[PDB]
Image 1 (cartoon, rainbow, N blue to C red):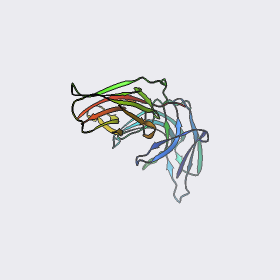
Image 2: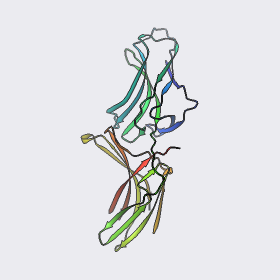
Image 3: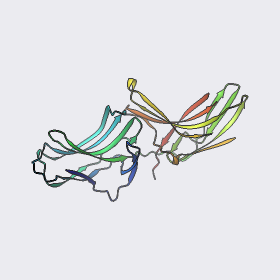
Length: 273
C-alpha cells in the first residue's frame, strides 16, 4: 500500500530546511507553537489475490527527542492521537481527514550530532507480523526578542605580567544572521607568539551522568586587529539550555595563544521578520 499525507494549508504555509541523517538538506513545512495541524491521509491498497487484514489505523502528532547514535533513548514530549479506522480488511483507496487543534510545540527542532529533536506526523497501520508506519517530518522554530543594541564584552587571555591579550566584541547575544564585530588589543607582549586565533565553537551536551556525551565543533576560526565573524555564513542554531534535561546546545568564543586559551559563552537566538 501507498501512504500520502498532505497538509490542508500546504499552499500558504512556509517551509524551512533541515539536515537528514546523511547530511543532505530537505525542505519541510514550518510550524510554530500553538498552530493547528490539519490535513488528509490517503491509503491506497493495491489489489492482491490474497485478503489483507489490519487491526487499526491511526495518525499521531509526535514531538520527541532522540538521544545517541544508536537512538537508544527516545523522549516523547508531545503525542496526540486520532484513530482513523477500526480493525478490518485492508482494501481500496481511502482518504481520511485529520485535525489537531492548537498544538503545543514547546521546543525548536534540532538535528545534532548525537541528538535530534523532531516533530512529525506518523501514520500507523497495525498488522499481525509488523505494523506499517509512515513518518511525515515537520519543522518547528521558536522565536526570540532582544534589543538591537550593542552591549560590549571583553575577554582576556595570556600570562600574568608577561602576556595580556584582550578581545572586545560588541554583544553577548547574537541572532543567527548577525555579525560578531570585535577587536584584539595587545595590552602586554613580553614574549613572542608563535600563533594565535579566535574560534567560534559549538558544544552539544547529550545525556547526564554515565550517559553524558559532549561534542565540541569549531564552527569558524580567524587567524589593533579587527575581527568580524559573519554568522549568516555558518549553519547555526539557537542556544538551547537543558531541553527537558536531555540536551544542551551552547556557543563560545575561544581565544588561543601558542598553549593559552580562554573561552566565553555567547547566546545565539532566532530573530523574527
